Amino acid sequence: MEGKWITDQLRWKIMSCKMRIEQLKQTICKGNEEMEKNSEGLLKTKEKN
Amino acid sequence: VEKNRKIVAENLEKVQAEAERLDQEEAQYQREYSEFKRQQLELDDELKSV
C-alpha cells in the first residue's frame, strides 16, 4: 500500500488542482465580467461628467 | 484581471466623486437662483405696481 498511498497523494493534488483551476477560471470569468460592468459604468459616467 | 478591475474601479470612483461635487454645486446654484428668482418675481410685481 505504500505505493498506492503515494499515488493517492498525487490524485488528491490532481483533484484539488482541477478544482483550483476551475475555481480560478470561474473567478477570472467573474473578474472580467465585473471589469466589463465597471467599464460600461465608466463610459456612462464619463458621458455623465 | 484584478489589476484591470482595480484600475477601472478607481476611474469609476474618481468620476463619481466629480459627479457628487457637481451635484452639490448644482444644488447650490438652485438655491442662489431661487433667491434671484424670488427677487425677479418681486420686481415684476413691483414694476407693475409702479
Image (cartoon, coloured by chain):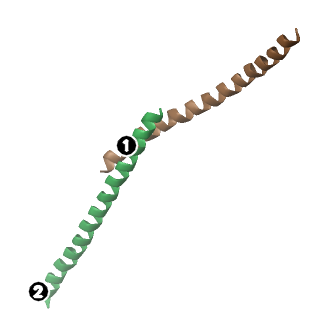
Chain colours: A green, B brown
Residue B16, percent from left and from top: 49, 38
Rate crowding at label 2 as few (under 14), some (14 to 19) or many (20 or more) other CA atoms within 10 Å: few
Q: In the displayed structure, would residue B49 be above or below residue B27?
A: above
Horizontal side, residue A39 vs residue B20: left or right = left
Residue for badge 2:
A3
- State the quadrant of the N terminus of chain A: bottom left
Q: Residue lying furthest left in this view?
A: A3
Horizontal side, residue A37 vs residue B18: left or right = left
Q: In the displayed structure, would residue B48 be above or below residue A29?
A: above
Q: Which chain is home to disc 1?
A: B
Residue for badge 1:
B8
Q: Secondary structure under badge 1? A: helix
Which quadrant holds residue A16?
Answer: bottom left
| Residue closest to the eye, A11 or B11 | B11
User: What residue appears at the point 30 percent right and 63 percent down from the top-left corner?
Assistant: A26
Q: Which amino acid does label 2 sit on?
A: Gly
Rate crowding at label 1 as few (under 14), some (14 to 19) or many (20 or more) other CA atoms within 10 Å: many
User: What residue appears at the point 84 percent right and 17 percent down from the top-left corner?
Assistant: B45
Find the distance from the CA under tag 1 to the CA under tag 2. Answer: 51 Å
Q: Residue lying furthest bottom in this view?
A: A1
User: What residue appears at the point 35 percent right and 49 percent down from the top-left corner?
Assistant: A36
Query: Disc 1 vs disc 2: which is toward the camera?
Result: 1
Q: Secondary structure under badge 2? A: helix
Same-chain check, marks 1 and 2: no
Q: In the displayed structure, would residue A7 be above or below residue B11?
A: below
Horizontal side, residue A11 vs residue B15: left or right = left
Residue A42, percent from left and from top: 41, 40
Residue A37, percent from left and from top: 39, 49
Q: What residue type is labelled 1?
A: Val
User: What residue appears at the point 58 percent right and 33 percent down from the top-left corner?
Assistant: B23
